[PDB]
Image (cartoon, rainbow, N blue to C red; front, side, top):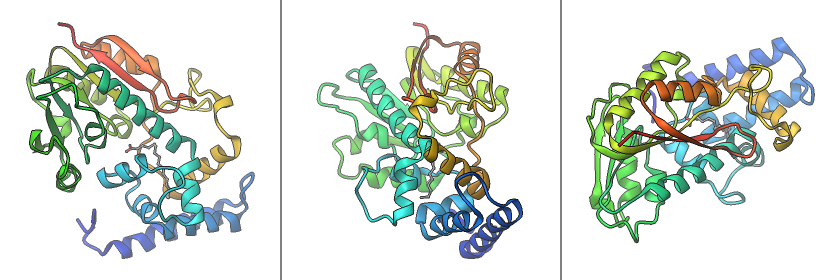
Length: 300
Ligand SMILES: CCCCCCCCCCCCCCCC(=O)O
């Protein structure tokens, strides 16, 4: 488990996080569509869920939960009723599954025989292990992650895979990446959205650029700001169910309080990537434009 190391049992910290969320409900009262009692029911649904508990405690996703959430097939599995609504209806969850699809299409398009593909942070390597390698013999896969549990999980997920022997894993802080021209393709999801400082994200992109061979490509992603937050929000409100958005807003803002709130526009992301040395940017937007994918080229 992610915790201890807080030196306490996770159950003790969880009770605290639940108490704090309950107080925020009681002190702030009703919201449109969800009275106090209903909010308390939502909090209980979170606390009864394995993923819900992880989010209450840690306020972000790790390798395990990114994989399990992103690869969830709607209607499948053993989920409690409310838990299933969270897995299947929240606009941001729908968006990250769309994004996952765009990552797969982009990586597949750019794959060539013998190429070296890196994922940073690799997590369980869900996207790379899902690709079709039938016409790309000799691909080498590289996974970098700072979480030893992520690397263990990648190994376990790849154990029966055709490319199990083509994987090299490294425990490294992604923010300190210093590979020089080692990869043809690099994919990254779930780092920039946790870093509110724009310059720190630009520097991460620069390390990605430095790690790519000339002519290589980066596939990454970013969460975008909603209309309340930015005059330049790309959100298509006609592509978002109003009630499910209200549900997400209550769950995120009041209950979980997620750490993935470094939201950036297409133009901001373009500026960062161009500063880092990338050209020929292509954006692959999800339907509501909550979580675009970007493919960025390093000049030959
Ligand atoms: C079942 C408990 C509630 C589940 C709530 C899941 C909300 C996840 C939102 C995922 C998309 C945006 C955040 C991505 C963050 C990341 O990739 O690390």
